[PDB]
Image (spheres, coloured by chain):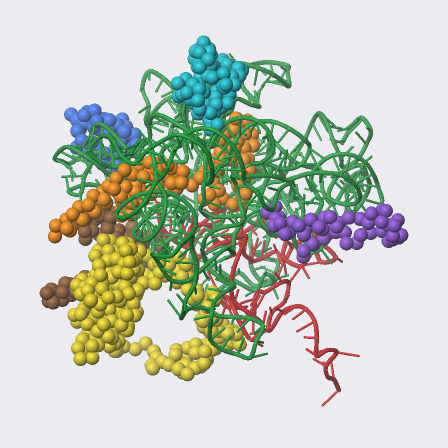
Chain colours: A cyan, B yellow, C purple, D orange, E blue, F brown, G red, H green
Amino acid sequence: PNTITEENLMKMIADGRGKKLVVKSCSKGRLQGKVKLKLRTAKYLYTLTVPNADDAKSIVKGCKDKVEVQYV
Amino acid sequence: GRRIRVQRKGAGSVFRAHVARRLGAAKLRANDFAERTGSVRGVVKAILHDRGRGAPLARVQFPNMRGEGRVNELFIAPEGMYTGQEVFSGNKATLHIGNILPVGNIPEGTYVCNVEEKPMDRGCLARASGTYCLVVAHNMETNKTRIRLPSGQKKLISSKARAMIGLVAGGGRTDKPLLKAGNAYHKYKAKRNCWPVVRGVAMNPVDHPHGGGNHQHIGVSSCVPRNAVPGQKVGLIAARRTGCSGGK
Amino acid sequence: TANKTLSRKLRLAKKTKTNKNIPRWVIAKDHLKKTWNYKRHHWRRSHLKL
Amino acid sequence: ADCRVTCRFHSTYRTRSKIVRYKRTPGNRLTSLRVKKLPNAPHCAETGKQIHGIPRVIPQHLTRQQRKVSRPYGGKLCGSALRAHILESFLNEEN
Amino acid sequence: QRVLRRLLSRYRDDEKIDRHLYETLYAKAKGNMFKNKRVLLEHIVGMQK
Amino acid sequence: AKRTKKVGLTGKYGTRYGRAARKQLLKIETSQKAKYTCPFCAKDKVRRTACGIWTCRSCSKTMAGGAYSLHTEPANAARATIRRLRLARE
RNA sequence: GAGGCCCGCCGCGGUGCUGACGCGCAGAUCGCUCGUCGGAGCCGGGCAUGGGGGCGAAAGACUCAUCGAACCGCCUGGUAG
RNA sequence: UCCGCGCCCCGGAGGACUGAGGGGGAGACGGGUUCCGCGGCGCCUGCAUCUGGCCGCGGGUGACUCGGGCCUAAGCGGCGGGUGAAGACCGGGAAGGGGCGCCCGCCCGUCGAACGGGGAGCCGGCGGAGACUCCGGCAGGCGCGGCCCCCGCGGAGACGCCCGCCCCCCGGCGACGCGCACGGGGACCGCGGCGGGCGGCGCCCCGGCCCGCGAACGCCCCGCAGCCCCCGGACGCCUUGCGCGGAGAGGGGGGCCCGGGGGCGGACCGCGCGUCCCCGGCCGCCCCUGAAAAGCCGGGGGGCGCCGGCCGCGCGCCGUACCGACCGCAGCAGGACUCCGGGGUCAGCAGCCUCUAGCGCGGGAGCGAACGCGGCUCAGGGAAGUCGGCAAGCCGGCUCCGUAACCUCGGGAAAAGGAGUGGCUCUGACGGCGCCGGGUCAGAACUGGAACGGACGCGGGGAUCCCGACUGUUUACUAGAAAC
């Protein structure tokens, strides 16, 4: 797995490159209050750790509705 | 009677040379047109230790004269060969240690090694550590050169026969006492199964001619004839004289 | 043995397949009276391929 | 309490290829991970000194920029050996 | 030996002692002249003065 | 600090091997482990890799030599002959 | 920090008890005691050398419980004052 | 051992034992179904059986990534041929190939290693029986196709970065000895704190115990030592030991390699001494110098023309259960290769106990004869016994004293001999200071039937003579010797 280089890379892949699902895990264990958006491209699983939940929402809108979005 | 140890040793099997992990056969550069009319030039890539030989062996790279590549030749190393030395092989090679020239060109009194016994033999004479042949005389009329072999014998060779100038390195190797049976074991492992040696007086009468009685004695003269058969030849072969006496 | 050859595995296989008692129905069909394979083997006592 | 890892390899004989290092898995058990023998990085044809720039990975998995050095004779010769050859070639021509 | 060398290097680097004095004290340290750092430090003060 | 009065590096062999062998070895093994002056880089760094093989630690030059001494006495005499005889021809 | 160095573990050998065992645990074991333990060391796999042959730090030792000449079949139901 | 459908079955509870070179968990070989579930006791389980490795029945071994296969080693087979009555043995000198008109080209191996070399696998879960194989997650390798695409740049330099191919050459990697010490990681360990759970509790107890997890891989940043660059021009730099420097030190600033660490993605917090494994730079050693080959990759020249990215898809063949079950007539106090290896006492991987895990062996009671075997002790004497001190016993750990003849000057030598040793209560040293680690080495009191290496482990010694210098080696199964 790898860490996506910001939302610019995340959404560029989600707009045109291979993408299957963007899973939004939320604050597991309260180690962090951030939300983790994870995209499964054919090659790797790319994760964006978003400090603010509101910031994640705008990034999720950027992901095409063709990409499946799941929330956990 | 059992086939004696000398009889068994010639049948190959376990008494063969331990030739594994050995550099190769040390020989002179093949006689060629540029060695007959001219001198080829080679750089000493590496001075290396052969497994069974005390003398060091040097890998000298020569240009390929029949191609675009380079030819690697393994030679006995004359003392003073250094990494990067430009050795020369040929009729017009200069008189410097490590150069190979025909012995007729070589002046008298010179110390040479790896001399060719016959023209174009790739070298057969002084090859052991510290050994050397001496150019004694040139007979121009017969095109033959007398050399003094390491045993002090003198032989007439062809003037064409080629030799490498210099004593072969590793000299004084035999001066150090082996000290322990161990050191002999190590040295003989590298060479062949010839150690340890059991005296035949120690053996049974079936195993050896010297055999075994009640008092551990040869019981007949150790001196054996030259025409003795393979089992019989075990003592001093065709001894012209025997005993420790001063002279010569 | 864990690293068995195929040829060896197939010869040993037949021995397990043929290590079977006479079927009871075959004894009734043939009226055998004697009821034992004899060619049957036991792993501890048998020395197959020896 | 009993960290006896057992054997990851097909045979127990511990040759140079069969070496294992132990870590902890996410499931709290000791694990055996094969330690691969690091390949030597290329060496100078003259000098025999590890050429700089190329990492000690099989060159099959390296990529061309990482398995090459940007200089004439970049991999075969070191920058001192190559400088020596440049000097001798020019100087021998003068004489 | 490591403890004595560590102090000597710092003193040379801080210019508390000269490099010639450091060499003389480093050879004496190798020769077992100084049993403990306090003896070295005392000798260094005496040599300086 | 003089650990042994007479036997030198031969103290390794203890009381075994005799006196004559230990005296010869003292001289032979002092030469074998001695640092010789590099004929090329003029630095006393030459050490014996193998019998007949001596390598300068600093020079990096490997030289063919006597088994226990970089230069054997016969070989020095041979070198002087060849140099004189070569000069006689030219 | 040297050494066919010394004590000593596994290992590898096998000294003594002339111990047990001797219709045995066993067609050479068991118990103590002991030789050695960085080395002419020890161990596994592959491989080579074959019978009047091999191999032997030599004891006519060893060569599948067989050795001053293996085992298998045959000559051979050899011959025997 | 007790109790319970109560069997040597099984379950619970007590008491044990094997004691991390395990009666533990796994492989190689060898067996060949012994594996697992259900039923059973006719056989076997040398007592018994409701037991089982036994009998019957029904099942069980899943791989692009592990191993074979593949490469070569020692070796072995093959080779126009050579020879021998043949069987067969022996072997280069022979018009011995290759994508390809052309062009290039002396001449074997699709033999041989389930320990050598090799392109790439990790975690979690699941089943009565299996897993690097299944399933879920997550990667890597190697092809193939579709599509897009296009053949250098930067730095003073070491080199950096944004990946061409073929031949012919020159290389590199595969690819390598041993050892003492030293350093760095990983695991293991221990001690604190903290959070959760227990147990015991006559007295004490924040003193006991149990658990607290983070893989391959992908990025980013460091990484001692080592090597190199650039300025410049010296007795300086340094190690445990060394080493190094006008053939270029120090100093300053950089490049590279480093089986490694941290961060992030995958997805409890400190701290210390050891152990074990790997690794690094050294140094020592040899009349010893420590394999090879596929495969892969650079460079030079030549010719040519790419590379790459993204997205699909594929990866065949065989091995894969189990082993206290192998081999000795046997479920034989007999052997038989490895891998992992906790705690205390201690110099110890010794001995003695124990955690984990395994487990209670071809049978049970009673009695307490001789005698045997394995031990324990013995007044006084002390080898008077005997062929001979055979056997036993003495001695022994550490610290400090103190050591003779002789000698090949290395030894002898632990010579010979003596003295101390426990527990408490303290005091010094020794690093990294505010702090904060250390666990060794001294010294002193005070105590105790006149006790202390309190078990354990663990030389008796001295004077001679003969022989062989020595370490070695040997008659497997009556001679270990002075023999070899």
Kindly identify the residue that appears in the image at 36 percent across and 80 percent down: B239
Residue C10, horizontal then vertical, whole percent:
66, 50
**Residue closest to the eye, G2 or D75:** D75
Residue H117, horizontal then vertical, whole percent:
44, 46
Q: Is residue C43 something one can see in this rendering?
A: no
Kindly identify the residue that appears in the image at 52 percent across and 18 percent down: A68
In the image, residue H112 sits, relative to residue H135, either above or below, namely below
Report the side of C48 relative to A29 (left or right): right
- Among the 4 quarters of the image, the one containing residue H281: top left
Report the side of H93 relative to G43 (left or right): left
Report the side of H329 relative to E41 (left or right): right
Residue G69, horizontal then vertical, whole percent:
60, 73
In the image, residue B142 sits, relative to residue H451, either above or below, namely below
- Among the 4 quarters of the image, the one containing residue H402: top left
Residue D75, horizontal then vertical, whole percent:
30, 42
Which residue is most to the top?
A54
Q: Is residue D25 something one can see in this rendering?
A: yes
Kindly identify the residue that appears in the image at 44 percent across and 39 percent down: D36
- Among the 4 quarters of the image, the one containing residue E26: top left
Q: Quadrant of the C terminus of chain B?
A: bottom left
**Residue closest to the eye, H481 or H208:** H208
